[PDB]
Image (spheres, rainbow, N blue to C red):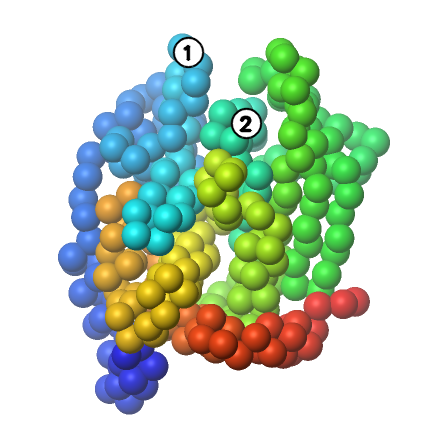
């Protein structure tokens, strides 16, 4: 049972140790495509690469490479695409992937600027009247609407394949208040955010996999997917007990390296899952308490 494990780990002060255990057990697979010299400028961080076996391939003859991994959680019947924050030259690739993969949602867990440095290109339009065109991939992107809340912003975007002139609505869920250092004090606002994404349909099997990114697409991105999947599994077999967060994390790590970057991110994942479990186990009232406690308006 995870809350007892949580308190035991807290009591013994052994988060760093548990986390290192995970790093040591984690899968190691080749990333040969990522490391080809022609792809050097498609990678944001030299230490964060997609495994060859799980990487998303762009459907182009030229260079099919993007730093993105399909994380396919069999038991939970949830898939996620984890990717890096787009680079100035990979914004077209990014939206190409969203198109080809049939995604409905993009979950962004970072700010464009953090710690006084650029963590991500401005890959979506900030004003309705100033649409973006990505010439390399022949796609058009238009801001349709935006709903700014205190800890996140949801945008409706229209993505057009300029080749065929089909259009889709993409929802952009932008968690804006992850702190520069550490993790959130309370998971409340994070859970409220996750539930907002869920509510939207973006995580659901009638759509392609949700695209999740932060700067590197492993830390915050890892935390989001881990929490979602754990909560889902707890739902599917109604048994907090059986769901082993460490085991789920290791399973996820078969598909992309580095998921959960710090011991404090691990601890936070536990907190989120534990607190989230309230809703899942029958206490429907709990979601209204997160909305109040997250302080979302203004």
Near mark 1 (Cα within 10 A), the count class, few <14, some 14-19 or many ≥20, is: few
| Nearer mark to the viewer, of 2 and 1 | 2
Q: At 41% from the left edge and 65% from the top edge, which residue is drawn?
A: 235
Q: Earlier in the sequence, mark 2 or mark 1?
A: 1
Q: At 39% from the left edge and 58% from the top edge, which residue is drawn?
A: 229
User: Which residue has dot 1 on it?
Assistant: 62
Q: Nearer the viewer, residue 10 or 285?
A: 285
Q: Position of residue 250 (x, y in %)?
A: 24, 56
Q: Nearer the viewer, residue 44 or 194?
A: 194
Q: Position of residue 166 (x, y in %)?
A: 65, 20
* Residue 160 falls left or right of residue 221: right
User: Which residue has dot 2 on it?
Assistant: 99
The answer for how far apart the CA atoms under marks 2 and 1 are is 17 Å
Disc tally is: 2
The N terminus: image quadrant: bottom left
Q: Position of residue 173 (x, y in %)?
A: 61, 50
Q: Position of residue 276 (x, y in %)?
A: 47, 72
């Amino acid at each position: 049972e995870m809350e007892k494990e949580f308190e035991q780990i807290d009591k013994s002060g052994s988060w760093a140790a548990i986390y290192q255990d995970i790093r040591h057990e984690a899968s190691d697979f080749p990333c040969r495509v990522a490391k080809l010299p022609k792809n050097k400028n498609r990678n944001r961080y030299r230490d964060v690469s997609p495994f060859d076996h799980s990487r998303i391939k762009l459907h182009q003859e030229d260079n099919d490479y993007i730093n993105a991994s399909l994380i396919k959680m069999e038991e939970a019947q949830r898939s996620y695409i984890l990717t890096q924050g787009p680079l100035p030259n990979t914004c077209g690739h990014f939206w190409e992937m969203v198109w080809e993969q049939k995604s409905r949602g993009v979950v962004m867990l970072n700010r464009v600027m953090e710690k006084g440095s650029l963590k991500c290109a401005q890959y979506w339009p900030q004003k309705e009247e100033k649409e973006m065109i990505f010439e390399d991939t022949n796609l058009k992107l238009t801001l349709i609407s935006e709903d700014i809340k205190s800890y996140y912003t949801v945008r409706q975007l229209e993505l057009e394949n300029l080749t065929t002139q089909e259009t889709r609505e993409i929802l952009h869920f932008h968690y804006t208040t992850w702190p520069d250092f550490g993790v959130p004090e309370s998971p409340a606002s994070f859970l409220n955010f996750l539930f907002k994404v869920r509510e939207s349909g973006s995580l659901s099997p009638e759509h392609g996999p949700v695209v999740v990114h932060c700067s590197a697409g492993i830390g915050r991105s890892g935390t989001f997917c881990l929490a979602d999947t754990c909560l889902l599994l707890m739902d599917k077999r109604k048994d907090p007990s059986s769901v082993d967060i460490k085991k789920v994390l290791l399973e996820m790590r078969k598909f992309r390296m580095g998921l959960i970057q710090t011991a404090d991110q691990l601890r936070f994942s536990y907190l989120a899952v534990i607190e989230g479990a309230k809703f899942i186990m029958g206490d429907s009232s709990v979601q209204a308490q997160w909305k109040e406690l997250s302080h979302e308006d203004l």
